Image (cartoon, rainbow, N blue to C red; front, side, top):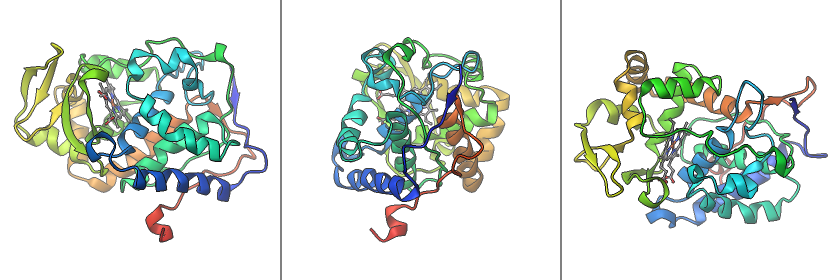
Length: 289
Ligand code: HEM
């Protein structure tokens, strides 16, 4: 099964920078969502969940086909709460109806990371909407109540190694958990991209508590929280080394995150030899907008 990228007809860098700007202006304007966190964190989670269905063994799932627009994937229990990200993007898609669904959902994640002062993430266009029958079944996204061995094994399906996994998990410095979405509650409610996930893991005094949904989570008196799969990164000696590396080197973390997140968003896609080079979008701030 091969998914060949095909550039939206006649479109070039300038077209996609217009779409980036539309998403970025809306992130700035619609600022009250989720108690003033804004939509940045949910758009990052959305880009990850539409990509995280990929299976390296048969090349099914992944961001290419934009299949989250179909009921089976939209209603996956693992995707509860992402409807808010979908509603945010819908008017953008109406304004630019030429962009494919996979391109829009993945570009939403790139725009959110950059506008939250994260690293630049190169991004390639040419995902093509595929039919409803290509939608992966539910149950490909990970559980949170597991240990390090589970996390490592899970991510082998997406062709990610230990450094890639620990870099990708740094996105958990953003946003919060919501009891009604996932059975977990709390978090720092942060909307600026930093390496604070690693600093908090190493520096806070974590307590294992049970929440109102009867699930265990790790809580600190500062108001931070970690899922069991987050805490597993300091229980496994290989993950722990890399957590310490990113707690001590913000630039290294930004560089490794950028590469792992681009790879996540591109898994399963074949880019022709004559495809355009990846784009690097300017932020609103760099444009003076
Ligand atoms: C073992 C892997 C992972 C598990 C089990 C996990 C699980 C979760 C859960 C349960 C939530 C809370 C959802 C809610 O209640 O609203 C969440 C939030 C989030 N996750 Fe993950 N996740 C994982 C990996 C990742 C990765 C790789 C990224 C992105 C690179 C990501 C980005 C996010 C973001 C940004 C949020 C906050 C969303 C918001 O504030 O609305 N996660 N995750």
